[PDB]
Amino acid sequence: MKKGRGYVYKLEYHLIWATKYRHQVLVDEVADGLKDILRDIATQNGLELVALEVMPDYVHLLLGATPQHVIPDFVKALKGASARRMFSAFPHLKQPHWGGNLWNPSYCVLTVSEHTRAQIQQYIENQHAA
Amino acid sequence: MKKGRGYVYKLEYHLIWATKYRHQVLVDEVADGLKDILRDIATQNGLELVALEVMPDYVHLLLGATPQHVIPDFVKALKGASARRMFSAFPHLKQPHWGGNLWNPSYCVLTVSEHTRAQIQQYIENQHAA
């Protein structure tokens, strides 16, 4: 637990989103680049990137935050800045055929539970892969 | 999980705060009234009161929220409106000797973990009782 001015807290969010059409582009050096980019962005927004997993068609972050952090703001920051920086580092991801890959417009945000793994699998499976 | 416009989520927060000086006033009909008041306020702020416990000197809520809910805002709503309504229902709680009881300025907010119970105990024990 961390202490702020008038409060004590420990706040972690699982945050998940997919590539467009679940195109399997987050591989090898691209996946490696995205990890670095996400670590930077988290830090730059005053978040702790507790854990991260990058699958070929999705990302799963575990973020430590403060009460004052607003989920939609930092989701937008993470998704938007990551898309920008990835397109700069990897121009090949600019593929209008695939809506430009980065990213499916949706996100999934979950606090910790015994069902997290299943929740994430459900969520990703509900994103259709055309 | 619930589904909103562009997102999927399940967000629960443990929210804890004490009476002033840990005065043990939240008992019997007072505790009962506070539960009703808190249920109402949670609902009125678009929160799901998943669970509640009222101890003589503190309250512990488990709150289901949306991404757009901002923790400090709803904390202030819950603490502020609860104090006002409890003073109205129970004027005897207006006790300047005890700074008026409702409430200690601090709060504790936690996402679920294996240590929640110990965290809440630490937090309450760190509020010092007159």
Image (tube, coloured by chain):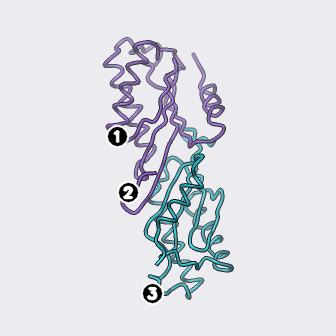
Chain colours: A cyan, B purple
Specify the amino acid type for callout 1. Answer: Asn
Identified at 40% across, 22% down, the residue is: B34
Specify the amino acid type for callout 2. Answer: Gly
Say which residue label 2 marks.
B4
Say which residue label 3 marks.
A96
State the image coordinates of residue A52 (x, y, percent, origin top left). Answer: 64, 62
C-alpha separation, residue under disc 1 versus residue under disc 2: 17 Å
Horizontal side, residue B84 vs residue A64: left or right: left
Q: State which chain disc 3 sits on.
A: A
Q: Are marks 1 and 3 in contact (CB under 8 Å)?
A: no
Assign a secondary structure to mark 2. Answer: strand
| Mark 2, other Cα within 10 Å: few <14 / some 14–19 / many ≥20 | few
Identified at 59% across, 62% down, the residue is: A60
Q: Nearer the viewer, mark 1 or mark 2?
A: 2
Specify the amino acid type for callout 3. Answer: Pro
Assign a secondary structure to mark 3. Answer: helix
Q: Quadrant of the C terminus of chain B?
A: top right
State the image coordinates of residue B97 (x, y, percent, origin top left). Answer: 46, 13
Identified at 64% across, 70% down, the residue is: A35
Q: Are marks 2 and 3 on the same chain?
A: no
Compared to residue B29, the image places residue A104 above or below, namely below
Q: Are marks 1 and 2 on the same chain?
A: yes
Q: State which chain disc 2 sits on.
A: B
**N-terminal label among 1 and 2:** 2
Say which residue label 1 marks.
B45
C-alpha separation, residue under disc 2 versus residue under disc 3: 27 Å
C-alpha separation, residue under disc 1 versus residue under disc 3: 42 Å
State the image coordinates of residue A61 (x, y, percent, origin top left). Answer: 59, 61
State the image coordinates of residue B25 (x, y, percent, origin top left). Answer: 47, 14
